[PDB]
Length: 54
Length: 152
Image (cartoon, rainbow over all chains, first blue to last red; front, side, top):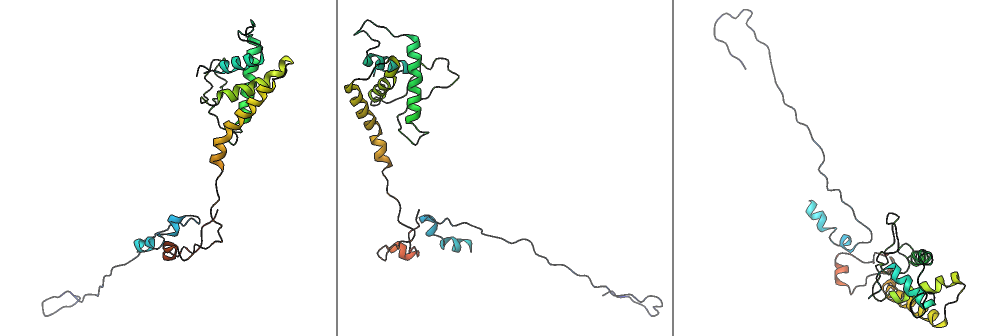
């Protein structure tokens, strides 16, 4: 708030002001990955991959 | 091996037949050599069915090189006898001849020997069916929930 000093304040009344800020969002962060059907290396480790993704 | 070119294979085939060489005074004629080189190329291109047939290391002539004769055949040491015996058999009908029984037998033996190692390599077993359990003895499979084999 502003503040004046004096006795007579004719035509010195101020107004009100209230600024603001904005918060937004960007883009998702993904871990898109694939699982080949016939793969031992894909059958194993597809849970360690989830942990590493987390 | 002293047999290192398509012309060398053709000379061996003609000598086997009895059309060239020094056992008789007859000499190799260029028109009878070009035809035999054509027949050899056709025979090996038929045997090597785009890689799904008999593998021998033969190197196929390119249209750029003027004489197909003169090039190395590219075979191994153990393919030469089979190749030129079968060539003699193939080119015998041109001279109204007939390859002798010994040449026919050697050609059969050589072709079979040529395909033997390829047959051994191609004798392979398929993987387990996709509808087949891994069993509870396979501890790693029971761990990462690999209850069934992949298949294909």
